[PDB]
């Protein structure tokens, strides 16, 4: 069976948060949403290219992206 | 003396390795590479925006980016 022990955390500028949340809601599963600090958590991704390219199409560039144990 | 304390590692598709290496080494300090697995190691960056926007202008979208000691 599965071992879903890791999360990917995307951090964006406040002005980009709502549109980043919309993108991740439509294409991934949001586990946590912290608008106050600019963080969005999804299931752990091994390859960031899909997300980075789609955010770039929205003119959004994360301040940070990290995968770690939840 | 000084030493390297921390590194930002940018990982790209093999086809993007040379152009990424040129961009990063021109605008940041290159510390090391791993060409076999498409990694470029630069002095650590607190905010990835500038690099991710500049790479997108070159039509480069990293497979991975991380910072480590």
Image (cartoon, coloured by chain):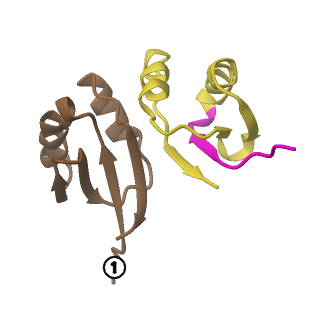
Chain colours: A brown, B yellow
- Seen in the image, is B56 located left or right of residue B18? left
Q: Name, please, the residue furthest toward the right.
A: B1
Q: Quadrant of the C terminus of chain B?
A: bottom right
**Coordinates of residue B65 in the picture (x, y in percent):** 51, 44
Who's the residue at 31% across and 44% down the image? A11
Q: How many marks?
A: 1
Answer with the quarter of the image where residue A51 lies: top left
Q: Which portion, as a residue range, is magenta?
A: B1-14
**Coordinates of residue A18 in the picture (x, y in percent):** 12, 37
**Coordinates of residue B63 in the picture (x, y in percent):** 49, 42
Answer with the quarter of the image where residue B52 lies: top left
Q: Chain of mark 1?
A: A
Give above or below for A29 relative to B13.
Answer: below
Mark 1: few/some/many CA within 10 Å (<14, 14-19, 20+): few
Give above or below for A53 relative to B68.
Answer: above
Residue topped by disc 1: A2
Who's the residue at 70% across and 29% down the image? B29
**Coordinates of residue A27 in the picture (x, y in percent):** 19, 46
Q: Nearer the viewer, residue A19 or A36?
A: A36
Q: Name, please, the residue furthest toward the bottom.
A: A1
Q: Nearer the viewer, residue B11 or B14?
A: B11
Q: Secondary structure at mark 1?
A: loop
Q: Quadrant of the N terminus of chain B?
A: top right
């Amino acid at each position: 069976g599965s071992h879903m022990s890791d999360t990917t955390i995307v951090t964006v500028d406040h002005k980009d948060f709502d549109r980043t949340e919309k993108y991740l809601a439509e294409h991934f599963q949001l586990q946590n949403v912290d608008k106050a600090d600019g963080h969005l958590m999804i299931n752990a991704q091994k390859n960031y290219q899909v997300i980075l390219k789609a955010l770039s199409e929205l003119d959004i560039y994360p301040k940070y992206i990290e995968t770690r144990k939840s």
